Image: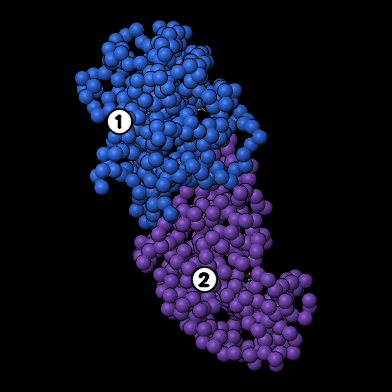
Chain colours: A purple, B blue
Amino acid sequence: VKLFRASEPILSVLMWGVNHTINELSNVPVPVMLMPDDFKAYSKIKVDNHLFNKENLPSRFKFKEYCPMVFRNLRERFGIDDQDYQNSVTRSAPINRFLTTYDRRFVIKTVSSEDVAEMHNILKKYHQFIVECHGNTLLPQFLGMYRLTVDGVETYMVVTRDVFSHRLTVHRKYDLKGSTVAREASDKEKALPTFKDNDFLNEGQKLHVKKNFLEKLKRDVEFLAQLKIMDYSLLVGIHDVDRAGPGEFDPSVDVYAMKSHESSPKKEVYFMAIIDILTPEQYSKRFNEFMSNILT
Amino acid sequence: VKLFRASEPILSVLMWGVNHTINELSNVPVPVMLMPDDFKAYSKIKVDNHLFNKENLPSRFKFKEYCPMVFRNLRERFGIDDQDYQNSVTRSAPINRFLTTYDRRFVIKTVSSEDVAEMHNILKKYHQFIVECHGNTLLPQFLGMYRLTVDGVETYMVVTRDVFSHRLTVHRKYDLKGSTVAREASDKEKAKDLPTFKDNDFLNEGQKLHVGEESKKNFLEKLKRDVEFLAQLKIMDYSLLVGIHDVDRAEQEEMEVEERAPGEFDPSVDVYAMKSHESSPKKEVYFMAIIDILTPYVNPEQYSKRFNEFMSNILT
Ligand SMILES: O=c1[nH]cnc2c1ncn2[C@@H]1O[C@H](COP(=O)(O)OP(=O)(O)OP(=O)(O)O)[C@@H](O)[C@H]1O
Ligand SMILES: O=c1[nH]cnc2c1ncn2[C@@H]1O[C@H](COP(=O)(O)OP(=O)(O)O)[C@@H](O)[C@H]1O
Ligand SMILES: O=c1[nH]cnc2c1ncn2[C@@H]1O[C@H](COP(=O)(O)OP(=O)(O)O)[C@@H](O)[C@H]1O
């Protein structure tokens, strides 16, 4: 019995909504392909209950899913079964505005309306790109995009596959941007930190192994730049096994994880992917040079 | 997998809505008992899709369910599973303003707004009646009540268990009220396939339902307390509906359709069904129940009395 009990009412509307739309979809046949209208489509539902079902949900809310057919197909191409998606959002409240499902499998980012319009500007070319690389990419994997309205105010969310493992605790994080400026991390933010370009540079961390990652990444960033996208960051995460199976993951679940070489001094397993692709040609080149210097 | 395909957008919406509300109800705990709020509660949902899922449902529709919890409770008390109710409304479209679920189990009537209000005025006492008789009534057994909005316009629908058997064909039917007034089936009506015969048609035909003692008392006591209850609510125009099933005729019809290549029933399911007396001429099976009870106010005391004195000797 999916009681939608959450940390705050918009989370329970989210759980209700993802549940509702995913069931709805279970009743819609998967087509032999997607169509232009599928990229201009949306689901909208409005709930006014009165003295009924109020114990955990609101009595008045709205839920809109953008291009449900396209995002369900994306879900299939990324290897996510729909009822696993549904279970991870609905079994227990998402946690911590940026959220993870209770099982650390997916992240739910609160997003500006400009970003929703950017998603619509790109989505056909993004889908064909997922098609052409058979999902082997490092761009964020978009699994749904929703708009919740509750108590009056609208909120936009983009669900995506987590860059990090849902199992192995990540021990250090770096948001590399390739800046010609010097994006360092704040003393305030230093006191698990988030290190940017200058600090992975003046830290001495290297990543050891092999090279087909460079093929995947360069394809991704040539694509993003060929679409006037900027401000994206490559996110890197180190898990030192030694802290205390260890360095044990399922490469079909953590599709971004990667094992160290015997070279590596510490016992490390890495996770890496591109993030924040919703908003310049020089950006791609500088970004790629800085990400080049990183391997051993 | 449910397409909700149907001949009319209205029916598709009815299937979608019964599905949605039963599924929503699935996640709501079953209370220890009902609070008064539940008797003035409702659940609305308004759908407006766009370029999505329009093969059968309209893009734009609304669906309201009344006192969903007391009708869930009623369903329980009437021995109907929520899953079953949902499936017989959604597995295939209902058929023929009146509707029947594909499996001939439940009936969906289009009613007025005032019928809805009248059901609301009486619902609290009706639920306590159904409670204090364990679901042993001739009264209609109300399973849900809804309000659909297709293409801008509202339709009110009341779901009820069928007085007729889902298996056993009905060969003759009567609608009786005990009116002093000459109530007879029109020459237009008297010439349908299964005509709906009124009182005079029952009398000029000398029809006698012969059920034998024990079932005759179940019936007479049920009818007595049912219509006393209806009277106390100042409710009128209710009819007793009786369908006659010809056992031998059905045996023959089945034989004639099996050539184209028992006489028993479940009172768990055909709740208004009664067998004919052992020493009876034709082996028949009857279905008898009161219907059309959502109309408030000679006096309704008088209507109770005349109705009862009539149906008292409809059978013997
Ligand atoms: O809870 C109730 N206790 C008693 N009586 C009720 C209750 N609930 C409804 N009634 C009556 O039930 C009829 C159907 O009317 P309705 O309300 O379902 O339709 P709305 O008025 O909302 O009009 P709308 O602006 O949405 O087009 C109207 O006599 C309405 O007073
Ligand atoms: O997939 C993820 N798993 C865990 N944390 C993430 C993930 N994606 C982003 N984050 C966290 O949220 C931060 C903000 O990233 P993003 O670049 O998308 O926001 P921005 O638009 O302010 O630059 C990331 O640097 C990281 O701290
Ligand atoms: O449960 C049922 N099973 C089969 N027929 C029914 C059932 N309920 C109603 N009917 C048919 O519908 C007719 C009209 O019933 P009712 O008196 O409730 O509607 P009304 O508002 O037109 O008078 C009944 O006389 C009977 O012919």
Residue appearing at x 60%, y 61% in the figure: A88
Q: Chain of mark 1?
A: B
Q: Position of residue B209 (x, y in %)?
A: 38, 18
Residue receiving disc 2: A79
Residue appearing at x 74%, y 72% in the figure: A192
Same chain? Circles 1 and 2: no
Out of A227 and B155, give the one closest to the viewer: B155
- Note whether A47 is above or below A158 in the view shown: above
| Amino acid at dot 2 | Gly
Q: Is residue A174 visible?
A: no
Out of B64 and A249, give the one closest to the viewer: A249
- Tell me if mark 2 has few (under 14), some (14-19) or many (20+) residues whose alpha carbon lies within 10 angstroms of its own: few
Q: In the drawing, does residue B276 fall left or right of residue A191?
A: left
Q: In the drawing, does residue B125 fall left or right of residue B55?
A: right
Q: Nearer the viewer, mark 1 or mark 2?
A: 1
The CA span between labels 1 and 2 is: 60 Å
Q: Quadrant of residue B306?
A: top left
The quadrant of the rendering that contains the C terminus of chain A is bottom right
- Note whether B119 is above or below A113 in the view shown: above
Residue appearing at x 32%, y 34% in the figure: B251
| Amino acid at dot 1 | Arg
Residue receiving disc 1: B249
Q: In the drawing, does residue A178 fall left or right of residue B59?
A: right
Out of A14 and B120, give the one closest to the viewer: B120
Q: Quadrant of residue B77?
A: top right
